[PDB]
Length: 216
Length: 219
Length: 11
Image (cartoon, rainbow over all chains, first blue to last red; front, side, top):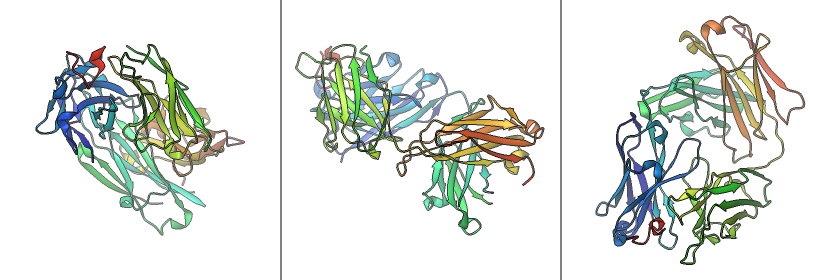
């Protein structure tokens, strides 16, 4: 099976450099062109560049907003493609995707899962987690995940055992520059005090794991 | 640079009814080699893009037959014959005939289900948060359709502006609804200068607006 | 523009 895995993303200071990798398996890597794309949060798809197979000269092409600053390279022996970014600006913040360009289908066909690059002066900060306690047929409760940077956070309820009724909202960027979000769940009224509800919050950029019990 | 103009930018489709999305390019996508370098992608919510159609009308392997494409020169159309919940997401056209490769702005497709009113819940700030010097009041609108809804904060009968933020979920695959949270943030000093905290909700599914209130420190 | 073709040498 065709496999593509982007890595290298994270928070980086403006002006600095960062190199992303696209590690591939399941095909003769050298025979294929590889392409990079990016998607700023909330925005559309954007082409970054591509690099041809060495069978066709191995040269690369770039979008206008990266020419000079970004270079795409490839290591056929390791089956890895690279995107080297330099002079990074805040407007370069995006999920960056690598893709195998087909031959019959001469476009990006197989896409990786992407890697988030955040270009910002701010520092990493873990979130505080506060309960949204239920009170006066159906009851609602949740957790408020406040003041963290950068994206993202993960939220589960009861270690994944509670999935029906769960809504985890997109993060909102506050006037401070820090993000917050809430996760809520609707449960039967009968299960208050009967069933225990704990929201599990993970913020990998901070290595923070908090399990907050929500009590009526 | 070739401009790719998609219309419409958003589509609400009754399940089982057809959808059609138009893509117009500023130059011809027909090359001298005889091929038309126009491609259609779908990005489902939270997922990587996936190819649907290549070279105007060819379905990519494994794409359901309800997807088809047509057109020539500068005008192209993607048709989904009977839309399903798994078809929700953003559709992009893309050209590869010229550098840079460019995309349309994306067309968002949702399921158009019957109107459903929100269930409203309010949550005062937690005593844990209050100790830290900030108070967040949260109003939750659960499982409603359409996405349009109005949430207004009122503190001792005075309407609030500029101190709340809203977030909305993607369309739920189980019932085709949305949910929304609105968070009012105040310094605890300002929070303790008022008593009544209410969020008032207006929605197409509500015949009369719905208010949820509490009094600070009375429950 | 042959430079848009990822599967040929543009020279």
